[PDB]
Amino acid sequence: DLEGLFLRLELAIDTVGAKRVVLDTIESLFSAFSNPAILRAEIRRLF
Amino acid sequence: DHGEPGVFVTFEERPEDIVNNVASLGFELDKLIEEEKIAIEHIAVDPSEVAE
């Protein structure tokens, strides 16, 4: 739920030597399983 | 000015972020924290790979 997004994002970042990033409709990915703190911690770690 | 030392307790932002925020206002918070007239402390529940 965290490592996969991190891995794909890092792969693409290294591909295009990204110095800018956009995250659109990240609201939907905030859908764990009725656990509030897990998604907050994932958000913080990603940022 | 009034010689009363103080401490800052942040629960969501980095001490570095706080100092950077007040930088542009001509406040030498970095100097104060390194001269021990003031302090900063960051407190958050779980670091990583552990339950909150």
Image (cartoon, coloured by chain):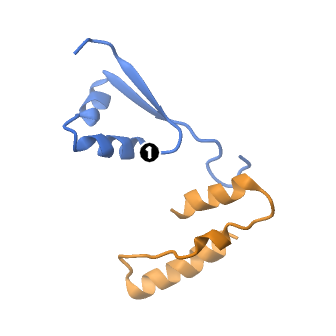
Q: Is residue B19 above or below residue A47?
A: above
Q: Position of residue B48 (x, y in %)?
A: 64, 53
Q: Nearer the viewer, residue B19 or B31?
A: B19
Packing grade of label 1 (10 A; few <14, some 14-19, many >=20) is some
The colour of chain A is orange
Note the chain letter of the blue one. Answer: B
The residue where tag 1 is placed is B14
Name the outermost residue toward the right. A33
Q: How many marks?
A: 1
Name the outermost residue toward the bottom. A15
Q: Is residue B16 left or right of residue A2?
A: left
Q: Is residue B32 left or right of residue A43?
A: left
Q: Residue at x 55, y 37 (%)?
A: B43
Q: Position of residue A6 (x, y in %)?
A: 58, 73
> Mark 1 is on which residue type?
Arg
Q: Is residue A12 above or below residue A29?
A: below
User: Label 1 lies in what chain?
Assistant: B
Question: Dividing the image into 4 quarters, which one contains the N terminus of chain A?
Answer: bottom right
Q: Quadrant of residue B38?
A: top left
Q: Residue at x 63, y 55 (%)?
A: A41
Q: Quadrant of residue A38?
A: bottom right
Q: Residue at x 29, y 30 (%)?
A: B34
Which structural element holds mark 1? loop
Q: Residue at x 38, y 20 (%)?
A: B6
